[PDB]
Figure 1 (spheres, each protein chain N blue to C red):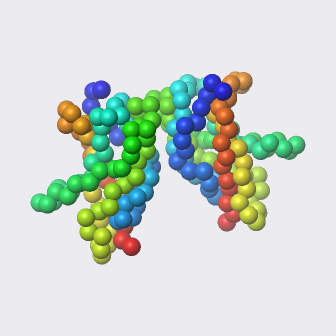
Figure 2 (cartoon, helix red, strand yellow; figure 1 turned 90 degrees about the vertical axis):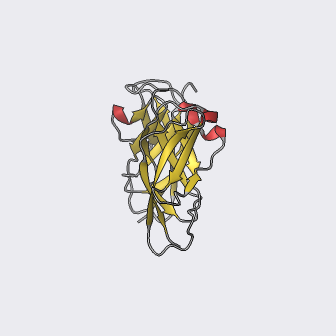
Figure 3 (cartoon, each protein chain N blue to C red; figure 1 turned 180 degrees about the vertical axis):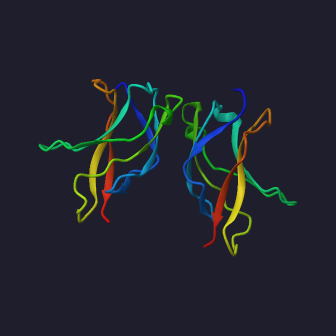
Length: 103
Length: 104
């Protein structure tokens, strides 16, 4: 609960990932942050937000590319959770929702 | 703050009717002392401003805003313009970026 996501560019996208999202957050260290996309279920899937250090703006924003879903053949939009977290870190932000769309 | 700077930004095109949300990452800015001015070199140097309350001025380094309707609603093709960050007091600006309005 140390980390926080204030606002996001988008909350949906192509299951193929590759979508650029602007993320407004509370202070974050550019060398110890990641954007984890995950599902809360026995399978426990997780993909990560793509981006280098330079995309973290003044420690208060992150411009990244979405990861793709593990199944491209989905019939309807699937919602998943996405949060902020320190690498190995055990510190995270509350988790917002992100939906993936078909093709 | 030194000199205004638009680091990067969301959209760079939208509808001539304005109303589109643009994320814009910039250098240090102060909530009640900054503006996002749209305009044209033109004789009639049209001018408009992005809409946003002071709450949309996230941590001094970013601005979430909606665009303003262009002055010609019925344009034949896509019309491009410059939109620079501007200071409400000093009056100084940031290098101007380009934004393109689209027809209905």
